[PDB]
Amino acid sequence: IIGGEFTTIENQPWFAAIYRRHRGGSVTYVCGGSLISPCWVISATHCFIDYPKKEDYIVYLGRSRLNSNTQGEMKFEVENLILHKDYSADLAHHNDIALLKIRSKEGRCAQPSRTIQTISLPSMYNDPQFGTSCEITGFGKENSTDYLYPEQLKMTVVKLISHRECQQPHYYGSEVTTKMLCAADPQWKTDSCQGDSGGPLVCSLQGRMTLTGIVSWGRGCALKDKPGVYTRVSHFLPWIRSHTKE
Ligand SMILES: Nc1nc2ccccc2s1
Image (tube, rainbow, N blue to C red; front, top):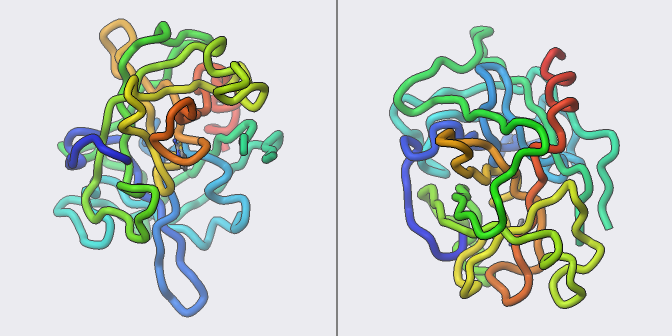
């Protein structure tokens, strides 16, 4: 997250931190995700496509720090890693959505607590109007030029951009489809960045906090006329519903 503010997991208790174990034993951060039911985390396919083997991954819930344990956190293995079969990449990632079925070493799913909660899905084809303020959360870079990721979780606020505006040549042209959502700051001063992929774009939809988007792609970070692009969750409900019975 470029700009914005530090936070803790109590302010985004559905946030999942996803790591990969290497041969040799070293563990590195992959991407964010969101707990949508006790056994299911939703994220982005592009985070996993190069290493599609479920055994490679570790998921934490209730974690506020990147490389230290948070009191109360839960650690899970990935029982199933489900990637979208229509995924494609050209800048733009199409159908950039993934499901992780989580399972602890003891065979259990997430147990809700002060630091671990689920986020509601939107109803179909129901999104906030352009100009609406939403929140994004992640452990991604704080500056495009940084090498390190922040040790503490961050969040910021971005505003939804209409498809009409995002499709202008001077924005992203045809790279953006109707299954994607653009969001940015009016001054371009805050944005998602490398390492934020897979995490939640959350909007309040009729009084309910709702998973409107999943961090997917963008040209650079916090650049004029280059918004963050998000998988439009409300266009994938049948896919999510079918695959969460797996
Ligand atoms: N504005 C955005 N920059 C990035 C970088 C990596 C992934 C997602 C995004 S969205």
